[PDB]
Image: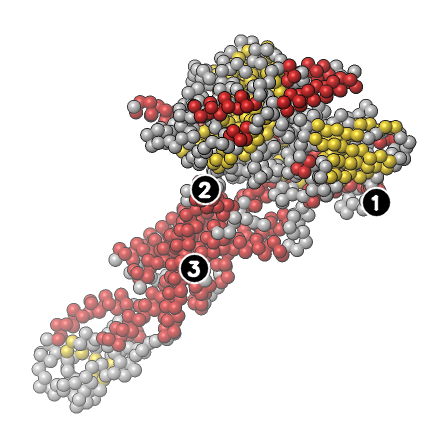
Amino acid sequence: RLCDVLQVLWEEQDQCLQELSREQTGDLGTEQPVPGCEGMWDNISCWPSSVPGRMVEVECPRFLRMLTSRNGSLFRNCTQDGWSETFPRPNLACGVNVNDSSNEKRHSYLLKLKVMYTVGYSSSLVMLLVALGILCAFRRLHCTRNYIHMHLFVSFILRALSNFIKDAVLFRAGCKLVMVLFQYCIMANYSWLLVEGLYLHTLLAISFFSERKYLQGFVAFGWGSPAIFVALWAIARHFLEDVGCWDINANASIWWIIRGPVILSILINFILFINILRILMRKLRTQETRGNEVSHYKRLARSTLLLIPLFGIHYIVFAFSPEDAMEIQLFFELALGSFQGLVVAVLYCFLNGEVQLEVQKKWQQWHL
Amino acid sequence: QRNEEKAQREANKKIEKQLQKDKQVYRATHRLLLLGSGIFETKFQVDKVNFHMFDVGAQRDERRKWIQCFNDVTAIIFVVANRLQAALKLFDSIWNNKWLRDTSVILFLNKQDIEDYFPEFARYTTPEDATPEPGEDPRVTRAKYFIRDEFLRISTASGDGRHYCYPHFTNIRRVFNDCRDIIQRMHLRQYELL
Amino acid sequence: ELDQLRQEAEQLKNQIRDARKACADATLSQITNNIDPVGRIQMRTRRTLRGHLAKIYAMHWGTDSRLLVSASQDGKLIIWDSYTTNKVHAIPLRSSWVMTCAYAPSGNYVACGGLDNICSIYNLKTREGNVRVSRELAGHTGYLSCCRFLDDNQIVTSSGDTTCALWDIETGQQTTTFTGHTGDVMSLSLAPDTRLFVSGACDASAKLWDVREGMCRQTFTGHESDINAICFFPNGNAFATGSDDATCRLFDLRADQELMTYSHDNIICGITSVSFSKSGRLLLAGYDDFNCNVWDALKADRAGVLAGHDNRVSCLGVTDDGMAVATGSWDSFLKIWN
Amino acid sequence: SIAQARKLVEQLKMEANIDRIKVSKAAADLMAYCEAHAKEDPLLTPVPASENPFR
Amino acid sequence: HSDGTFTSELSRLREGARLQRLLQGLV
Amino acid sequence: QVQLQESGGGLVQPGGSLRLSCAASGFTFSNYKMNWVRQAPGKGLEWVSDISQSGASISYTGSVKGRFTISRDNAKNTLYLQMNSLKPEDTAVYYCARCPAPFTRDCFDVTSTTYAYRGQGTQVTV
């Protein structure tokens, strides 16, 4: 609308601009050219001079006729004083007057949520660097579990920092590149959450298929999932009515390339979460456990709570929902879901005392 | 000077890349140990899974120094047949070992017949999951289940909780289906999962 | 006979009691602590040696401290360069679970053995492009525990047969065997001049033998149980001992009496290996509480503490001149303390 | 041990037949050896930056 | 997904705000 | 030098009682556990009793449980084993035994042949 009307105005303003010399200068005003009902270019309306009397027709803008019911010519008061400019009324400029609806509150609502997740990511981008500062080079305690968590922590860092760039650019090759790259960075996180979920389940279903070769396959399946859909999303962008930097994501007919791979990734991670929990439940069914023997709630509650932030299952809280009528869904995934990187960082780098015994060696070596 | 450095680095990378040629092959071989040349070894693959079971009975009877070297084996195989009391006493020391904490032990049985050395099981309760299909008379039911609970009583009274035992009944398939559970507990406990 | 023979055996022991008590005319505690200490000496992790699939169990320094060999438990035998951490050879083995490895002082052969009861020697002259087997020294009834090369013709082996034996490379047989131990012998140490050697079985009975005559010369006792590692003085007139008693002791070869006892109250872990320094004042010993500890033999004080590993140290060793110390633990890493 | 019981006499007599010098002389020679040879060893002495090529 | 709708809907309100300024400012 | 000296025994009528003693020497009794091993004529070595270093967790075998008691004294490093109702199957040579690794709860094969941490032992008959 904005870019459409701006381009239509630039293509139409240079057209009747020559009539400015043909109005109030040409077509001599010997026909009672009142000072109000005069012809001139006002950059808003382009109307010619007329004689005083009853209503006189005007030149409605073709880009604004659809905004009102009278999709054609319009008339204004042309009395002894005449209409000075557009005859201000409900049909002020041959179109809607205010056209404001639901934007007086949702605009401030989105602004309050905007500052919410940015300050949340502001502390998340530094928390991950503290969490990544352990598994980066400390080979005193390193194994295959870090070989998967490393990529996941990198994906959270890339996604959190990239969100801090969207406001400075959107709020040209700039928006053209930063848009497709933003979708790729988003899908990189959901895909790696699926790979992490697929990795731990495959390690339990078939406990012998871990011979250091599926890692290269999982890395390819991880970084290669967004590199395919977003690429297909980017090429189809130009081939199907490329307009602006593609802020038209409301087109659900074509947006399946993005929302599609996401909802299935959460769905597969959901069904895998049931299988992994079922296998863990089978381990509790043995009377050889030390701490708990009857009250399964004492262990399963403190076990699924650790797996929820790592699996990112909380995204399913409002999946398969009427997104077109559930604008409040952002509160679950943007206001609270922004800290997902912070929870997975504090749970796998501050808890899990195995990573605490490693840094304790440096703590004792400092005083040694 | 670069003549000797490049040649030495060439043999270095030629050997480092050799360790990669059998590293995954080594980890794919889940070693095993069987308790009652100086050592007997058998090899067999079950469903694309390698198993190198060793027999150390040919060594010295004293097991104070050579059993410490077996901290790397993933599963120990124990068998039984007053030797019955000494077999349980040996199981206690293996359980309460300082270093043998990550090697879950498997317990087997054998055909036998013993009642006069342990007069306490005369009042032992009936088995809760008895298997009377082979026609077990109440003698062998209470006897087998008493020695069964005796080994289990040892594995619950002491220990830190990082290894368990797995009795069985009357082969190789029964070991592979149980060794899988040991690997499952290994890859699951690493992720802080209770 | 045993009614009188065991009585004469006990009566002879009292003769040993009054013998060792008669030499107790002075104490070494006053002589050792009436001098100046040296304090802490800085030791840093200069190099780490990765590249092992399993945990190591023993090492042996090379000829001129330029190289060192380590034996992994999976079956690999690796030779390393101390200067640039480069692998020289990666000779495989016929079986796994080794427990000892010896490096010849001439650098021509390398020996290794374990539960196989077979001591194998390997020529170091690369004819076929790699290392090949040369001779297998089978015949024992128990596992081998320690081996030491005297020359390129002679080699002694400590094995679970409760009897040490001297072997000749020419034919590979027990030319001379020693007897008089109670329990499987676990470690032996060779004198620097190759003129004497001592061993210790699982009875804390450190008994001295002759390299040229198959007979016992001296006997040492005083550890509670399970002596584990022995090392001679740099000159050869004394030797320290490491046992599961969580305390080290120093014995001499002249007065035949326990000289000093290195014990502490804040240790509940047994000793696994022990090695001397070039000067002899420092005693290095690997503990079972995941850390290393060096003892001042002339002060009986914990001069310094070395840490970095999270598993038990199973081997030690120093250069041929006291330049650097090699410490290997079950972490599969070989950290060169220097 | 009845047949090999002779070891309890011929072997334990070794400590009684060998000479045993007093410990006051066997102690001074040892500590003097450590003090005299405490100069050629890189250990026991702060290693200067010019030495220790193993860095 | 979530972030996609938020970026799209907020940009639409940003466009509507500019159109309102264009309305009150030019017509 | 460590030495294990036992005392008590001799021929007694069946069903009697006795108090076997074990005298520890040469090592610290406060850091080690103790065990008792008997040997029937023409049979091997069988562990029959034990005790912890903390003076608790006393255990026995089913064949001597109840009619056999073991006691220790850290003040004198002594060990006392008293029993009653001497059976004909109990006629065997008993040996005082100790296992290495003090301050630990694990030691293997104390009844193994050619073991030095065992005294000369005494015998009892019916």
Whether residue A241 sits left or right of residue C88 in the image: it is left
Residue furthest right in the image: F13
Check residue D1 in the rendering and tell me which mark sits there, or answer none: none
Q: Which residue is mark 3?
A: A338
Q: How many marks?
A: 3
Residue C296 pos. (x, y %):
49, 32
Q: CA distance from mark 1 to mark 2?
A: 60 Å
Q: Is residue B16 visible?
A: no
Give the chain letter at badge 2: A
Q: Mark 3: which amino acid?
A: Ser
Q: Residue at x 36, y 58 (%)?
A: A163
Please, is residue A81 above or below residue C96 in the view? below
Which quarter of the rendered picture does the N terminus of chain D lie within? top right
Query: In the image, residue A270 lies at what x, y percent?
Result: 53, 54
Q: Are marks 1 and 2 in contact (CB under 8 Å)?
A: no
Mark 2 crowd level (few <14, some 14–19, many ≥20, 10 Å Cα): few
- The C terminus of chain D, quarter of image: top left
Badge 2 marks a residue whose secondary structure is: loop
How far, Cα to Cα, is label 2 from label 3? 41 Å
Q: Which residue is mark 2?
A: A368
Instruction: Classify residue C189 by image quadrant.
Output: top right
